[PDB]
Image (cartoon, rainbow over all chains, first blue to last red; front, side, top):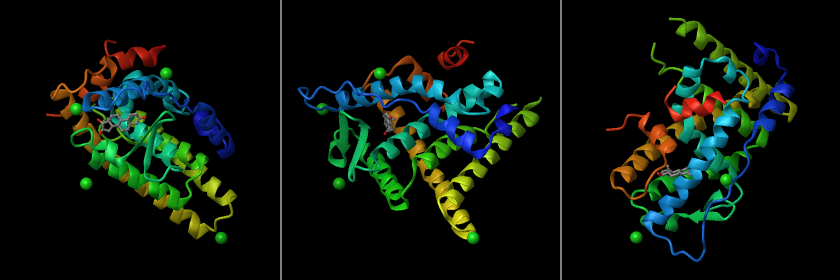
Length: 244
Length: 11
Ligand SMILES: C[C@]12CC[C@@H]3c4ccc(O)cc4CC[C@H]3[C@@H]1C[C@@H](O)[C@@H]2O
Ligand SMILES: [Cl-]
Ligand SMILES: [Cl-]
Ligand SMILES: [Cl-]
Ligand SMILES: [Cl-]
């Protein structure tokens, strides 16, 4: 139960150390965009990030204390939300653009290359705009990302000791909550402002969930149309949502 | 023990 005995500062340190690297896309500027190639680039990248994400998850305090089957469920539920919040964060400093990778920066018109995608882009762009308005800090972002991992899936658990097991997840979520407040208190926010920013931050997660739900149906539509061949991990990740 | 994700979580 080491995760429940961390100070806020140690919690923050642990999450910062855990952060995965920023990967490059296989984008070739000498290749003219098509629906297939764009979806090819995005899925290839996402497929490479999933591996790093799995390794990041193991470093989130509390996560390794769960059973393997719990760990699988949380990740199956959250993976696209986690990709999206990382994207939105990377993009905060590039208005009107999404920084999928440092060599792959797309605007909304380039999203129109893929059927149904531009509406997802617009929401992702809107979320980064909100992050920029709020002046979201890196220490707040790594708390939010971990909250997404632990929260998405915590209530859809199929079930024993399930109850007792979930109790541990809620204790960690509470620790992350304390850590956020700690951060905000340290930055000089009054009590009132602390509760207000905490709520604003957590209310963004609702939108991130909605975007993930929409993105998931879009990905599934791409698979069905055979637009791009999807990797076996990404397929498994997608199929876990049991769409149509 | 058959899912790819399960395998990668085990390493
Ligand atoms: C799933 C997705 C391709 C991969 C994208 C993707 C790829 C890498 C990454 O780091 C983040 C994202 C977030 C957006 C993802 C797209 C949303 C859908 O409209 C589309 O099918
Ligand atoms: Cl890579
Ligand atoms: Cl085309
Ligand atoms: Cl338009
Ligand atoms: Cl005060």
